[PDB]
Image (tube, rainbow, N blue to C red; front, side, top):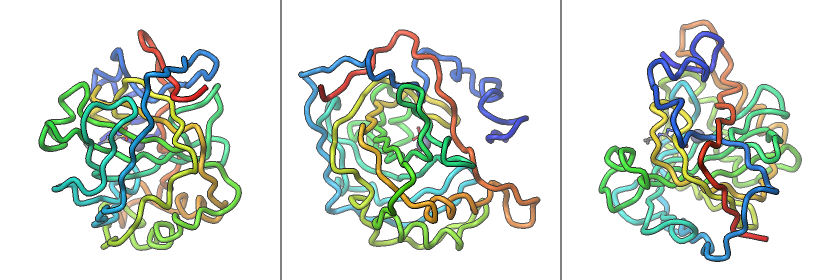
Length: 257
Ligand SMILES: CC(C)C(=O)Nc1nnc(S(N)(=O)=O)s1
Ligand SMILES: [Zn+2]
């Protein structure tokens, strides 16, 4: 199975998922001086007031919080998007040390972690259909740097001990993802892909310029998770990030000057 190790990591994924070498792969380095301000871009509309979180799960490659996506409860619209995108789940990518962990980079800078809020276009009816469409998904990416704690992240951090190994899940109701968002919704956007297999080229990426700060204690709890299932040799879930991929024939647009 694919993973992040020497023998099954990102450099191997193309063998099972040949689109890994495709024309719109993610993540990418965001060269801030080359991204063009696009005044036609609209402000992002993040409507999370009615979000219904359901469960938190260790899937062997990250941990994810899943939401009820059977109704327009927590939706993303505006920005570069046409139509309405329902929040399905969020998860993180992080490093073994604070100097790596993000998937996107900014002028080659790596952040300690990156949060992905994954949404799918309601015109396609379900996420499985959406993944087969070039505009099927919108992933809101938020960088994490280490400094002050993020209070809205603590409820997530405190339950991670109950999902240490692959396959574990827990009830995770009444979590408000608005507590994970930075002040500014200034963003970069570009057409890309899922960053884990199957690497489908179905995503409009919306990457916020402003990171959130999390504390060393919060990220250290991420690093206690395990890639392995219970009973297997313990392998810390760290460095679950795909490196930046070739930009190829793509322009990154900025919502801000
Ligand atoms: C629910 C399912 C289709 C899903 O969300 N799959 C993802 N695969 N990579 C993602 S990422 N790291 O680009 O946000 S999301
Ligand atoms: Zn992700």
